[PDB]
């Protein structure tokens, strides 16, 4: 604990150029025997590096003398730093020769020092200049091409074959450069004012009085916060000289005015309900770190180097510019020469928490509101303050530049730490829980294994997005004047105000991005799932958000694209959902008049779209069907709107493929069919028979649920049971007012149990695979080991559930769903990478694959192909061998590891289902 803080303290002092300050602490700690024991070679090297950059040869020699006094043998870092300081001071050749004589005798080879001990380019250059001055020639190692993954699944993606057509964005290179400059200013400020879409309040004395009081209050808060920052900085500095670890350099990394402004912005943004103190502290620490990194890059010229590099990179992503040899974005960034920043790595979690907590305490204490403190400590905004904000109705609402989607193409994920936002540090793992373990597995793993995940994430991020003007205007009209809950636009009206605020933020961002093209990067999850980095405007949020968001890129519909759009509209409405595709197209032809009338008069018309399950998506597809038919050639028409191709229960499909089941294949459309089979309906029928049995039993849950087990409710329960770790299922039951809501929770639980039993009874492969996975997970957790496994792609995935040791039951039940999510992510990533080779634009929303109408058929075929290949590869056998080699090889717990050996060895036997027919399955992703 303390050692990590001390190491963080010394690295932070290098960034603030507070070398005397850091050295004073080091000397005091060295004097104390107990503190000296904590002191380590890495800390000594950090002080050495700072003094070497400062060029203080005498100070560096004193640090080396301290190293000898401790008795530690100087490492490669120590010698690289001594050489760099010698270069900085252009010291005589004899001293450099004596330093190289001390090296290797007690400093290892100079080649090893250059290859390892990664340092800033200035540090390397100074060390090399010293070596050049000294007699040795240094023998700089030559550069070697980056390793390329040889895995069979990824072989096609990473092959050197030239028959590839990588997509290029329509926007010109110069326009992309201007967008880059706008994004760079956004990152610089980490704050962008966005106009509110709420109807402006009439100007009045009370509203104006509230605004004037608020402005005076903000000025007072600013002054008090600045005074508090000065006082805290002085106290921390006094502690540092005294000899006690402080957060003074952490506070100095960012300017006092900037820290005060960020604190005031957090106070403003804090919602009426409030936010957890730990979350707020984490947010403040991460923000301080991001703004510091931005400042360091601009002052040190990393921003200038980034401008040059990124401008060169844009040629690949700009249609007008051309690159002679096609490459993936990460490969391009690597061939150009990734400028890896050292600061990219974050502070230790204790230090981050301490900093965030201190800033939050400063905000709470400093801010005072006449009735006293604005913030109450689970921080709660003062009720009068919330009322004042409501009366003021400020036109502009400031959001974080990270929260807003980037106006520039996302930077390639050359590494987990270095990707997405160019100036703000973005970790690859979305999940906060078990973040350290999640990324430790990623880093230990060879880079080639994670290349596929990085490339897929970059490809999903690269896709352009634009808002729909017509949909946005109609939604604004409904939102501003009252609201339509059934349609999905929140009314002004706990949950209600939060929903209204969420709609306000999303619509405000859409208004800000009224006609600009915005790029949102995609951040992975432990389950390998892909989630957009922008929280406010991610497409996953809602149906209205999906309707607003359409691909900026324009794709010709093609000969069958119009048919795909009409089928998509029928699917979106949900009418005739389990009938053949030809029938769905025919139904679209039958309901075309309603389709057009909805497209033309959403508010005052037939309003047929409102009846459909997804009203806004139905309206958007209506608009694109109207535009298609109106256009002289529908095939020529460019349809921005995404076309979605989900595949029933993907997890159930994975289970049936993993353990070959003929009935399972037929039920989940893994076997060629003409009459599509609804899995949800079959499971509902089994639930109904079990319902009759329970009705015979004393329990009345069945009599309560009679006639109240709809396909939609069974759908939610099936998804939860398979690819879920219950709230949605109970909510579905609540919607039915007729259904006795006295047993909503009881009914949800009973439904979950019955659906799980039904799924196991109908599907032999599903029951066998689930049973083996659950038993293996339980017997792995038994040894205090969280069940980790490598996906077929090669990405490490580790379950993060912990109890303050692994929980045997949480891991045991979680493992089948997490494994299913890992397979789903692997299948989606293979589909995305192959589609990228084809040139298709692929984005994954939840479990649904989204692409342009022309691209739907090719995406479907790629999906089928990848699925076949994936399952044909021995997923079960490889998992069994992997888990044996990992957990079973445990001398400490060998006694139960032998029983785990037996359990893993008894893999579920495959049945008799041919995977090849999946390709010929029409309804697999229809």
Image (cartoon, rainbow, N blue to C red):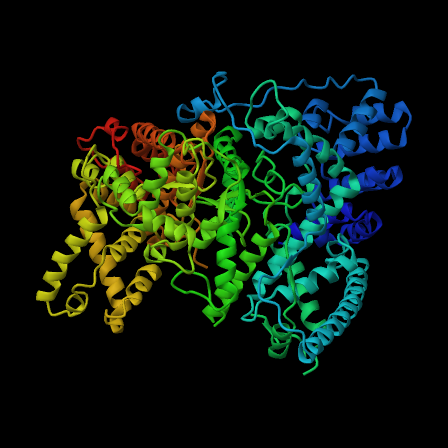
Camera-nearest residue between 348 and 869: 869
28 lies above or below 140:
below
Who's the residue at 51% across and 25% down the image? 166
Camera-nearest residue between 521 and 619: 619
136 lies above or below 74:
above
Who's the residue at 81% across and 27% down the image? 99
Q: Position of residue 120 (x, y in %)?
A: 74, 34
103 lies above or below 502:
above
Instruction: Decide if residue 176 is on the left or right side of residue 82.
Output: left
Q: Position of residue 696 (x, y in %)?
A: 8, 65
Camera-nearest residue between 460 and 511: 511
Question: Could you tell me which quadrant the C terminus lies in?
Answer: top left
State the residue lying farthest toward the bottom: 371
The quadrant where residue 422 appears: top right
| Residue 907 shows in this picture | no
The quadrant where residue 152 appears: top left
Who's the residue at 15% across and 53% down the image? 685
Q: Position of residue 682 (x, y in %)?
A: 18, 49
Who's the residue at 45% across and 61% down the image? 489
Question: Could you tell me which quadrant the N terminus lies in?
Answer: bottom right
* Number of numbered callouts drawn: 0
Q: Position of residue 710 (x, y in %)?
A: 22, 58
The quadrant where residue 558 appears: top left
Camera-nearest residue between 505 and 256: 505
| Residue 624 shows in this picture | yes
């Amino acid at each position: 604990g303390q050692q990590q803080r001390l190491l963080a303290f010394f690295k932070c002092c290098l960034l603030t150029d507070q070398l005397p300050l850091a050295h004073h602490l080091l000397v005091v700690h060295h004097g104390q025997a107990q503190k000296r024991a904590l002191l380590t070679l890495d800390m000594y090297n950090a002080v050495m590096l700072g003094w070497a950059r400062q060029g203080a040869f005498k100070e560096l020699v004193y640090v080396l003398f301290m190293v000898k006094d401790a008795g530690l043998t100087p490492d490669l870092l120590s010698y690289a730093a001594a050489l760099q300081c010698m270069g900085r001071q252009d010291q005589d050749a004899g001293t450099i020769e004596r330093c190289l004589e001390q090296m290797s005798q007690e400093g290892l080879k100079l080649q090893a020092l250059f290859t390892a001990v990664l340092l800033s380019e200035e540090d390397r250059a100074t060390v090399l200049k010293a070596v050049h001055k000294v007699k040795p020639t240094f023998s700089l190692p030559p550069q070697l091409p980056p390793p390329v993954n040889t895995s069979k699944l990824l072989r096609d993606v990473y092959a050197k074959d030239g028959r590839v057509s990588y997509p290029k964005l329509h926007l010109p290179l110069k326009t992309l450069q201007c967008l880059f400059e706008k994004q760079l200013h956004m990152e610089l400020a980490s704050r962008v004012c966005v106009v509110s879409v709420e109807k402006p309040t009439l100007p009045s004395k009370e509203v104006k009085h509230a605004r004037a009081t608020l402005a005076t209050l903000r000025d007072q808060w600013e002054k008090a916060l600045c005074r508090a920052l000065r006082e805290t900085k002085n106290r921390l500095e006094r502690e540092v000289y005294e000899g006690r670890f402080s957060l003074y350099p952490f506070l100095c990394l960012l300017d006092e005015r900037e820290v005060v402004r960020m604190l005031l912005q957090v106070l403003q943004a804090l919602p009426a309900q409030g936010e957890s103190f730990t979350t707020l502290a984490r947010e403040l620490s991460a923000r301080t770190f991001s703004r510091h990194v931005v400042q360091r890059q601009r002052v040190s010229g990393q921003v200038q180097a980034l401008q040059n590099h990124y401008r060169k990179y844009l040629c690949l992503l700009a249609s007008d510019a051309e690159v002679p040899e096609p490459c993936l974005p990460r490969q391009y960034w690597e061939e150009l020469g990734a400028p890896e920043a050292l600061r990219e790595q974050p502070w230790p979690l204790p230090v981050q928490m301490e900093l965030g907590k201190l800033l939050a305490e400063m905000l709470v204490q400093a801010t005072q509101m006449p009735c006293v403190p604005v913030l109450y400590h689970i921080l709660k905004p003062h009720p009068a303050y919330v009322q004042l904000l409501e009366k003021a109705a400020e036109p502009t609402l400031t959001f974080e530049a990270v929260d807003v989607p980037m106006l520039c193409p996302p930077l390639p994920w050359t590494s987990p730490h270095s990707g997405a936002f160019l100036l703000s540090p973005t970790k690859l793992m979305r999940t906060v829980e078990g973040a350290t373990q999640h990324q430790e597995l990623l880093e230990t793993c060879p880079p080639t294994a994670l290349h596929g995940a990085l490339d897929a994430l970059t490809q999903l991020g690269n896709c352009a997005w634009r808002v729909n003007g017509r949909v946005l205007d109609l939604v604004l009209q409904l939102f501003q004047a009252k609201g339509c809950p059934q349609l999905g636009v929140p009314a002004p009206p706990r949950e209600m105000h939060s929903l209204r605020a969420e709609a306000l933020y999303r619509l405000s961002l859409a208004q800000h991005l009224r006609d600009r093209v915005f790029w949102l990067p995609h951040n992975m999850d432990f389950r390998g799932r892909t989630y957009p980095c922008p929280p406010h405007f991610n497409h996953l949020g809602s149906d209205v958000a999906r309707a607003l968001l359409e691909f900026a890129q324009g794709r010709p519909l093609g000969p069958h694209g119009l048919d795909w759009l009409k089928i998509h509209l029928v699917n979106l409405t949900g009418l005739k959902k389990r009938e053949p595709l030809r029938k769905r197209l025919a139904f679209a032809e039958e309901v075309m008049d309603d389709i057009l009338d909805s497209a033309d008069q959403p508010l005052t018309g037939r309003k047929w779209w409102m009846g459909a399950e997804e009203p806004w998506q139905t309206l958007a597809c209506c608009m694109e069907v109207a535009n298609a038919v109106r256009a002289s050639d529908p095939a020529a028409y460019v349809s921005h709107l995404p076309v979605h191709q989900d595949g029933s229960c993907n997890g159930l499909q994975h289970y049936a493929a993993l353990g070959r089941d003929s009935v399972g294949a037929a039920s989940v459309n893994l076997e060629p069919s003409d009459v599509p089979q609804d899995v949800y309906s079959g499971v509902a029928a089994q639930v109904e028979v079990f319902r009759r049995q329970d009705a015979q039993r004393g329990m009345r849950v069945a009599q309560v649920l009679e006639g109240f087990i709809t396909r939609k409710v069974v759908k939610q329960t099936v998804m939860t049971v398979v690819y879920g770790v219950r709230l949605q299922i109970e909510k579905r039951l609540r919607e039915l007012s007729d259904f006795p809501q006295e047993f909503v929770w009881e009914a949800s639980h009973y439904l979950v149990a019955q659906v799980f039993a039904s799924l196991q009874e109908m599907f032999s492969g599903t029951r066998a695979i689930q049973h083996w996975l659950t038993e293996s997970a339980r017997l792995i957790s038994h040894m205090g080991s969280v069940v980790e496994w490598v996906t077929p792609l090669g990405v490490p995935v580790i379950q993060p559930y912990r109890l303050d040791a692994p929980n045997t039951a949480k891991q045991a039940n979680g493992f089948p769903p997490n494994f299913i999510h890992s397979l789903d992510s692997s299948h989606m990533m293979l589909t995305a990478l192959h589609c990228y080779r084809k040139g298709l634009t692929f984005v994954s929303v939840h479990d649904c694959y989204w692409t342009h109408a022309a691209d739907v058929s090719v995406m479907n075929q790629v999906c089928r192909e990848q699925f076949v290949r994936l399952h044909s590869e021995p997923i079960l056998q490889d998992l069994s061998r992997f888990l044996v080699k990992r957990f079973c090889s445990e001398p400490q717990k060998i006694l139960e590891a032998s029983q785990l050996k037996e359990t893993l060895q008894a893999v579920p036997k495959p049945g008799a289902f041919d995977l090849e027919q999946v390709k010929r399955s029409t309804y697999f992703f229809s």
